Image (cartoon, coloured by chain):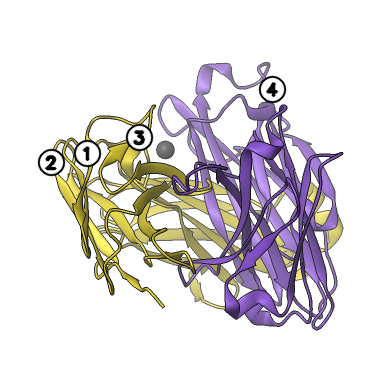
Chain colours: A yellow, B purple
Amino acid sequence: DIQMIQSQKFMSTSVGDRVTVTCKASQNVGTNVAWYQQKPGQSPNALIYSASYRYSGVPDRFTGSGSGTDFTLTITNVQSEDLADYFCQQYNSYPLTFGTGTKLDLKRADAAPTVSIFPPSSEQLTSGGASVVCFLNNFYPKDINVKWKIDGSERQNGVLNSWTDQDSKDSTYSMSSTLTLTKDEYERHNSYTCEATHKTSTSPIVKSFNRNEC
Amino acid sequence: VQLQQSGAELVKPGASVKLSCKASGYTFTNYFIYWVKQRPGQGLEWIGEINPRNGDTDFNEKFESRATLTVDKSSSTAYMQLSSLTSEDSAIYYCTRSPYGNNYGFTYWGQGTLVTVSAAKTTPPSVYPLAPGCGDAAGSSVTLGCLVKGYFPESVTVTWNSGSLSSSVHTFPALLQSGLYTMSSSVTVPSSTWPSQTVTCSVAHPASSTTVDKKLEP
Ligand SMILES: [Zn+2]
Ligand SMILES: [Zn+2]
């Protein structure tokens, strides 16, 4: 019955700055509060115990505070490796309950996407399949549009577009765009193009190949 | 890894699932074992706890009726069984622990087991190499990749050169197309290394117990 409320689903900051994650308990929980860090594709890592004590091994820039019902995780010197979800937990009374989490994102300068295009593999072809792939790498901000054109006509059906989590090293994003086709349709047309339009250019970033060649 | 959790599993609707969690060293009985659930939209939810010393348990009342927690001290293993599964039970399940004396909070978390409740069949991934071709050299760097297509359920882990190249790696989350998942992975290497310094992607799909390695051909 004790609810831990993390009212901020999202927090933003810049490298070097501070960030403050808040957690509101519905009843008093003294200082029986723990904080956890969860990086993408990792299990949670225990950060703070007893509201304010840091685990052996944890950087000094993580500070927890509070008592009763209001609890705070402060990260004073945010590095790019600090991208993660952070969540509180109470172990004052049963059942153990957790807040719903706050995800940190980092601000950085705008940056343009590097584009690579890949024709269907031979293995895929002998299997009866045809996918064409474009990687748009290391851009910022997140927002980006990709268009596929086959011999100059837009194709929308069959396109899967997927963003990575924010990059732990440079705070950029990357994106994969896959155009899925039948083998027969693929072997009938020639010119395959992905066009990425991103804020950092009024002109589309383009990569293309011809099947009849390459 | 102190807490070794069983692999991702597909479970049919209404059947049971039994997960395992193996503890390391000679420290099994120094801890309470806890199970925690995460449905990728929601938050963490505490399921239950067990005492390995005698087998005593405690539960979140929400989960108690369909959950059985046991232990094997001889093999130092904790087990959680859940019965009558629905789609709402599809989630990742963590094995965790905290000191037997005081509840620090959870000091170590296992890697977690993604359980998918679905009537569908298990389908292993086809792995396709993404080698650089007609594309321009892209400067002094070359980006390679692997397309992982037609698998069910989640998830897959893609690694490059058996764990080696793991700073230049981008991992794209899987999407559904025709009931099946597709994801991709890319790695960037200096272009001067390409032909002879070979590059291989290794794709594990726990749920179908399949591992496919694919050498990228020059
Ligand atoms: Zn990167
Ligand atoms: Zn055509």
Which amino acid type corresponds to the residue marked 1 in the rendered image?
Val
Label 2: chain?
A
Disc 1 target residue? A78
Which amino acid type corresponds to the residue marked 4 in the rendered image?
Thr
How far apart marks 3 and 4 lie (CA) works out to 25 Å
Disc 4 target residue? B198
**Coordinates of residue B211 in the picture (x, y in percent):** 81, 44
Say whether disc 2 or disc 1 marks the residue closer to the N-terminus: 2
Which element carries disc 2, helix, strand or loop? loop
How far apart marks 2 and 3 lie (CA) works out to 16 Å
- A190 vs A88, left or right, is right
How far apart marks 3 and 1 lie (CA) works out to 12 Å
Ligand 1 is within 8 Å of the C-beta of the residue at disc 3: yes
Which amino acid type corresponds to the residue marked 3 in the rendered image?
Lys
**Coordinates of residue B69 in the picture (x, y in percent):** 74, 62
Q: Do the residues labelled 2 and 1 touch (CB within 8 Å)?
A: yes
Disc 2 target residue? A17
Which amino acid type corresponds to the residue marked 2 in the rendered image?
Asp
Q: Are marks 3 and 1 on the same chain?
A: yes
Say whether disc 2 or disc 3 marks the residue closer to the N-terminus: 2
Q: Are marks 2 and 4 in contact (CB under 8 Å)?
A: no
Label 1: chain?
A
Q: Nearer the viewer, residue B189 or A24?
A: A24
Q: How crowded is mark 3: few (under 14 residues within 10 Å), some or many (20 or more)?
A: few
Disc 3 target residue? A169
Q: From what the image shows, is residue A78 above or below residue A202?
A: above
Residue A188 appears in the picture as rendered? yes
Q: Which of A69 and A206 is in front in this view?
A: A69
Q: Which of A86 and B196 is in front in this view?
A: A86
| Dot in front, 3 or 1 | 1
